Length: 98
Length: 99
Ligand SMILES: Cc1n[nH]c(C)c1-c1ccc(NC(=O)[C@@H](NC(=O)c2ccnn2C(C)C)C(C2CC2)C2CC2)cc1
Image (cartoon, rainbow over all chains, first blue to last red):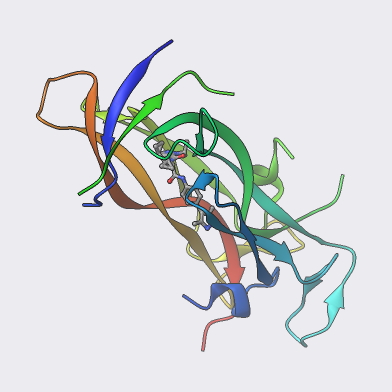
């Protein structure tokens, strides 16, 4: 029960040179703001070494960020939302295994 | 300039450490902003950690930047009313080949 008013009028190629490079995947949800979210997906299980080979002794892992979205509530009523918490992959890094 | 109503009642730990491009979180607090607390990544090194545990400058640690929205109180100090703002946030670091 904590309601506020929001004006929705608003204010690299690392993915490619990274030893843990990634692609983006589109998710669209018309009941959600933002409706389109791009999620990072690691290209490889391992990490690319200085020869351009995959080395599976290291791991590409996605960096997951807690992020909020607006969900329409009650549904289809266009002016009114609840804040939701989701986990989104924003990129990949290379970790030494445990 | 569409205005909407929002209910603010809401719905792998150690990468920062095991990464060849490791990083720390900096807390930035702004009481005029929701969320007021944002944790930003900063790369520990300009280079990347190699298999021996040393900084190797043949490669670069770079921040992963994500465009994110925050709520700014408008008019200021009025606690229940906001405009959406766009900012750039570092979420972590990756290791890139230079050119
Ligand atoms: C479009 C797209 N592609 N890939 C991603 C990820 C996204 C993509 C998806 C969603 C969003 N959401 C936000 O920006 C929300 N902001 C946060 O969640 C936020 C702000 C500060 N700190 N945070 C985190 C760190 C807690 C925002 C709500 C949607 C209006 C603000 C109100 C609370 C931003 C990009």
